Image: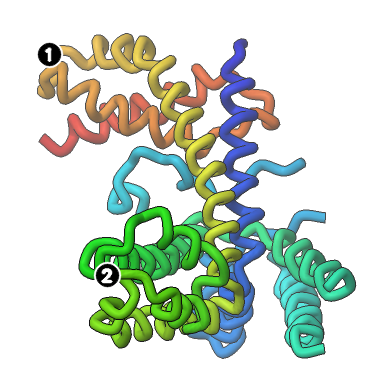
Amino acid sequence: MEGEIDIAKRIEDGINQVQCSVAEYPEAITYLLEQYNRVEAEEARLSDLITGFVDDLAPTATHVGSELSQEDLDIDPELAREKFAELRAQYVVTRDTIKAHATAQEEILKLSEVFKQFRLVPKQFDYLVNSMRVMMDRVRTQERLIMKLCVEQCKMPKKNFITLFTGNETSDTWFNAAIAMNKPWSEKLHDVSEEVHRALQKLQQIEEETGLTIEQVKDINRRMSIGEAKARRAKKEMVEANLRLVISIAKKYTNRGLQFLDLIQEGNIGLMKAVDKFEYRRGYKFSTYATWWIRQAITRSIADQ
């Protein structure tokens, strides 16, 4: 046995970070209760929604940092009825204190601790995690646009733009002040007014959709990325540390119908799946765990040609 437990524990930590970031996203919460309002009206199956409940357990968001393509990547009825009830009751209470910061924040930190009890099934965490990235892409589209209009089209140098937008980033309050600074690039910004207003009004929509501020959506996302990058990096090291293994097994299916470099492509896809599904807590030797996956991808592939 090896420090493959140490990469393993690093993979796990990065994946928890992503899960904790999902738990900070309001839309992840609603969607979870919306998907249960699909299980009880039977449009969906609970085993495709969550795995079980936590009261450390291994992460269920197994797809984070995986190098396999998204195409290769694809509960007692009453306890489940109880928990989803506990989520729904705690939600509608937070949904109110949002209207009525230290006390509200301690409940916001609790709706998130209740959400984290749900061991969502991989594909679902994938919906959430992508859901969030696409939203961060909208924030990013509008902010880059705005800087191009101000900094490039109207000639406001970078320095001043940073200074103004970098605050709240949503109300006109920051823009009309650029105009009101009456410097050479100020009146010019009138040729950029409506396009710049619509962005801010589109940026405000993101905040309304998400139920966060632009700075928060960015926050959670930045934190998610640190997690995604830690797991990704760590899985890459697990796959790279086991290419000896892959070559070893492939050398066993040598003149069996599939040529070498293809034999280690299928071997490697078996390894990347192994690196994903593996759990160190279970006490088994990775080397052995990987072998069933590596081999299966190799034999399986030999059967198709």
Q: Nearer the viewer, residue 30 or 198?
A: 198
Identify which residue is drawn at 56% across, 43% down.
227
Placement of the C terminus among the 4 image quadrants:
top left
In the drawing, does residue 51 fall left or right of residue 71? right
Place of residue 247 in the rendered image (x, y in percent of width and height, measured from the top left): 29, 12
Kindly state the secondary structure of the residue where label 1 is placed.
loop
Q: Nearer the viewer, residue 91 or 156?
A: 156
Identify which residue is drawn at 59% across, 60% down.
22
Q: Amino acid at mark 2?
A: Leu
Q: Amino acid at mark 1?
A: Asn
Res. 81 image quadrant: bottom right
Q: Nearer the viewer, mark 1 or mark 2?
A: 2
Placement of the N terminus among the 4 image quadrants:
top right
Mark 1 crowd level (few <14, some 14–19, many ≥20, 10 Å Cα): few
Place of residue 242 in the rendered image (x, y in percent of width and height, measured from the top left): 41, 16
Asked if one can make out residue 79 in the rendered structure from this viewpoint, the answer is no
In the drawing, does residue 37 fall left or right of residue 304? right
The residue most toward the right is 103
Identify which residue is drawn at 83% across, 75% down.
104
Classify 66 as above or below 74: above
Give the Cα distance between marks 1 and 2.
Answer: 62 Å
Identify which residue is drawn at 54% across, 69% down.
214
- N-term mark: 1 or 2: 2
In the drawing, does residue 100 fall left or right of residue 60? right
Q: Which residue is mark 2?
A: 149
The numbered disc on residue 48 is none
Q: Nearer the viewer, residue 95 or 171?
A: 171
The numbered disc on residue 255 is 1
- Please say if the residues under marks 1 and 2 sit with CB atoms less than 8 Å apart: no
